[PDB]
Image (tube, rainbow over all chains, first blue to last red):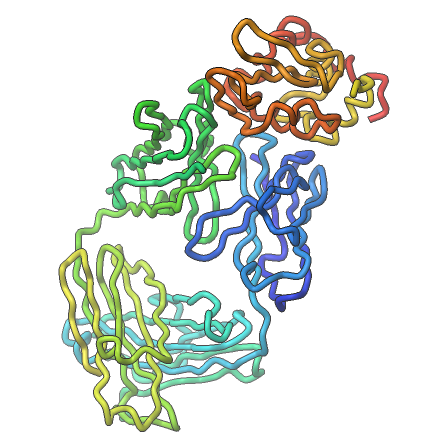
Length: 214
Length: 210
Length: 129
């Protein structure tokens, strides 16, 4: 099966700037490469067909070029409604295959996350469970690393994360990280820590609490 | 103009069959080639296959043997059948023209053996309920429910600013979701803050004061 | 316009027909030769109210619309007139959709009769592609 590699995985730009997205085929496919846009909560939309053919009804700022194994989708002056996912697809050989996609996101000023940690509620403990929750809100860029620690030891098992899409209100990103243990496990330890490493600081933001206090 | 619409069971049990219908309007189902495309969780698209005017079909080899695409000229619809599914078949399914000029809104099909389960709703408040600084964020953890979705509000909707409600994640066959709300320190605990969680599938709606 | 053999071959290559769904360039050059002698304006009336248009003689009963053919299905969703252009873009796009059906290039009788199973590669040999 033909493999399509799109790069970069993500691109952050300011509306008004122009951009170029790449798509490479593992085998030559001539001009049988198509470009799709897919916004959040929406289905894919064909933008360019057969590498460079324009689609009537598609804004002129979108154009495509390339041939063989190297293709490029160009957007002259990205507009506010142009942010989302972009995928290339080849129809030269069956099965038709899609690239991994490139995410076009909005560029804004860096912002440190606001971190908050929460202990298991009395209710959950009563039911025999224990989830430790950490919120990391309104930060930028999206790239972030969250590490959990119990009694000074990094903990990976039991951790589940959820990320919101780039915020419609301020273009930042938010994240939720949950450490789930049983009541017995939780009660065997003392210090719970949520550590966030982000571009805004060389020192990680640390939020914690001890069961032996407060 | 031509429009497509997907419809069918949103939940399929492992080992069973997934069936979807694509209703074509504006044009005849025999006047174009038609296909099915699915989108897995991490923006992974797979072209499942298509049916051309002669009735001939092309199926993705990864699927091969499990998939079948058919059509009904009198109803102006075409279908997708996918046997012996597993959780890996959970995805958003789309029907579209072979040319890619027309797409249906798409429909989510989840493969799971879980039964309808109302969520447990837990309050999230700072250890030893005291604020630090000018603002404070509180939270709500919705755990162990099925199927999606749930609707979460704060103070029955009277508190709507500074809220972040995250997408649910699958935890042990069930879903878990959390929501944070940030208010000024002069707001809480002075004023009551309650999490309202409704789960349609189970006809339940619970309130949780923080 | 009437293309030269090699000129059309290069054009078809530019338009991605070489190895499209497993069909080497020769196949398309040979098919164009027998169907219209490389003439984009070639047309042909059929017993029914359908007409074949272009370098690859695509039918108006199934593939294109001319606004005057009974039982038009317009599979290629294109005006038949677009298939008579000096620019082969439309004819190639439609040919690709036709060949994407189960019977591949068998949709062209002339191809089966004069090209299928032959050394089609001879049709582009001698050209500077």
